[PDB]
Image 1 (cartoon, rainbow over the protein chains, first blue to last red):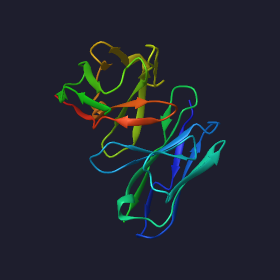
Image 2: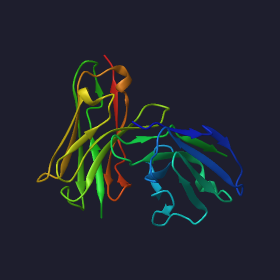
Image 3: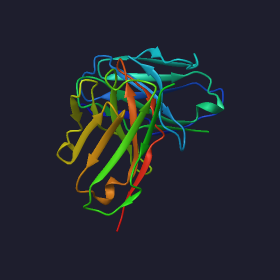
Length: 106
Length: 116
């Protein structure tokens, strides 16, 4: 069972700023790592899968990278629409697990 | 159009059983996986288990002995059942479609409060 840890847990940032969030795996996930964004009272939305691929209609301001046990999500020049929670999830064998989440506040 | 809609019991007393229904529209259950995820108040997402298109299942290690997942391909429904509820089982429960290493569509979730 791989545990995923996210950092930071919270981050305050202003519109237009550039941020990076980290997801660390307690074991090798072999790039089978996805990211999701969740806004308040809504369900999580897929952003990135297999470490670097953006899902459909995800803005180009988002990018993921990583391998092994370390992964990151970079958000270029934040838009008001980007505030919310961010979660990483692995797909290496089973069970699957999610990191703790990062809360991005304005 | 892919649609996932969860219906649950609302409040339930501790030690009872819970059954949640995920009704899917627009795709076939034989073709995709359905994962169950919960969100405890104020906390993150917790992976509960899944059922593959072929009926195999997998579960969270910690909760495995209290969970069962099944589905009715003809009714287009996936079920989640959890025994011996604890008050800390209070959470938002979600079903999500899986395809090619990603949960691409999610239901809006159903809130379950464990109380007596």
